Length: 514
Ligand SMILES: Cc1cc2nc3c(=O)[nH]c(=O)nc-3n(C[C@H](O)[C@H](O)[C@H](O)COP(=O)(O)OP(=O)(O)OC[C@H]3O[C@@H](n4cnc5c(N)ncnc54)[C@H](O)[C@@H]3O)c2cc1C
Ligand SMILES: *[C@@H]1O[C@H](CO)[C@@H](O)[C@H](O)[C@H]1NC(C)=O
Ligand SMILES: *[C@@H]1O[C@H](CO)[C@@H](O)[C@H](O)[C@H]1NC(C)=O
Ligand SMILES: *[C@@H]1O[C@H](CO)[C@@H](O)[C@H](O)[C@H]1NC(C)=O
Ligand SMILES: *[C@@H]1O[C@H](CO)[C@@H](O)[C@H](O)[C@H]1NC(C)=O
Ligand SMILES: *[C@@H]1O[C@H](CO)[C@@H](O)[C@H](O)[C@H]1NC(C)=O
Ligand SMILES: *[C@@H]1O[C@H](CO)[C@@H](O)[C@H](O)[C@H]1NC(C)=O
Ligand SMILES: C[C@H]1OCc2cc(C=O)ccc2O1
Image 1 (tube, helix red, strand yellow):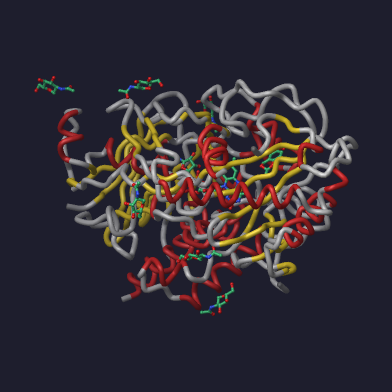
Image 2 (cartoon, rainbow, N blue to C red; image 1 turned 135 degrees about the horizontal axis):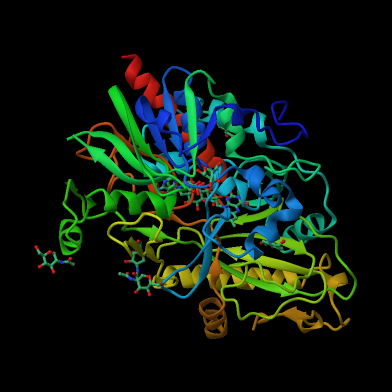
């Protein structure tokens, strides 16, 4: 861990090659166009820019416009803030009725997220069947980690929860480790030890400033085709249209996220033939899987209200089993809810410091889809449905996770945070529904599910893409973001998708060097 980032201010040096999409002089030909300045898209664009002329198009603005994105303390503020169409948090509600958010900002979800950093479970690579260059994967993790990842300092709540996971039998003790492994560990964070957020936008500082151009408030509406992708149409904040193209052996990559990538493919006539024909969208490339296999790992939780104040913390201490991944954060109270922290706006608000104690279902096996709400306007959010707990294996895994949270609440570690010194976990004061017979745990899992925010899928490798992230049947078109896999790489996937953007950039540059 010689290589990890130090405490430092958020590096906005890259703003020297960031322009308003209102600038028509950005229109023209590039070697690469990357759609979406987010978790995968920023490192992808930085990496291609080492050798080639790159245009990165981001629909949001720069994070300096929203300073509460740049500190650990600001996390809740960005979710509390009303969505006016400009804000870094975009609010949505799945058709399941569960409140959710996605990013709208240069840096993508790494600018608004909970900062937890992990590398992929090392069994993930073989599970995919992709011929990964594993040495290069690890060099690329170090490239990300040297820029924006730290070893967290001690936080009293994270240390309580770590002792509790160990006492609850989530073994072994892995100490400090970036790796997704069974047991309890301190992992990395993209918040530094002064609370400064570091993010994917900082990876643009690794780009060649003579080769990389970024347009912000660039809403990419259509991929243009020859069958080859040739370019994009994008609109600016004033509503005017702009075109950009790729040249020679160049490519368009879609990095618009689980929601934005399938949406743009569909709008561009890449998607299921009967569905697109039903909307009178001319089919450029029939593929029955665009917007299919869309996943949201369940979050289930209790909230305890200790009788004495607890210090607020960012999540750094993870409890990992194959069937559930658990963490806890401690928070100040609030009178405005952070949107999607609880599954609906109609949720009791805490009046005192509280601990959010959570469990994540792996996979999940339940899936849904993304469909268009507008056949024309990319600023109109698509419909999304996850079908939480439609697969009974997911419900069984939540039962196991909820019993383990019961074990955690029974530990000597957590005993001092009880309101009453009674033998039972009814000694805790709860915000919302306390833990409750498999049927009671089943009801609790179904009724109180929230989003883990780790949604993925909709443009899967093996369905829409080949093992090189190419859209099947289309030249010069790739997708690189969380739309690409039907299972998590680990409990906290930002690390994997930061790595993936640069990795695929390197694979593109290698493919082309021959
Ligand atoms: C609140 C929250 C907390 C999280 N906490 C953690 C955590 O602590 N650790 C962790 O590992 N994971 C966390 N995650 C998940 C993780 O951050 C995401 O899964 C990951 O960042 C997704 O990366 P992506 O590149 O697929 O998407 P994004 O990073 O969202 O990138 C997509 C980008 O495309 C842009 N865009 C979309 N459509 C268009 C268009 N048509 N034209 C132009 N631009 C477009 C978007 O504005 C966005 O910037 C969290 C998620 C959320 C929402
Ligand atoms: C782009 O320019 C317009 C005026 O033409 C302005 O309203 C908008 O804020 C600018 N956006 C950014 C990201 O600078
Ligand atoms: C990659 O690094 C991981 C730890 O994250 C290590 O377990 C593994 O052996 C490394 N693999 C290779 C190919 O070096
Ligand atoms: C598609 O267009 C045809 C006209 O060619 C029309 O009959 C039909 O209603 C249209 N469907 C939609 C959904 O626009
Ligand atoms: C590691 O990933 C594999 C999937 O290939 C999965 O079977 C296993 O449950 C994971 N291990 C942990 C501890 O999450
Ligand atoms: C579009 O979204 C609205 C508002 O959420 C929804 O209720 C409506 O049914 C959707 N329309 C289509 C065509 O999906
Ligand atoms: C759950 O998913 C698994 C594997 O994807 C599959 O075996 C089974 O068909 C699914 N069960 C349900 C209820 O859909
Ligand atoms: C487990 C974790 O999930 C996120 C989270 C956010 C807040 C707001 O600060 C507070 C607590 C919290 O707990």
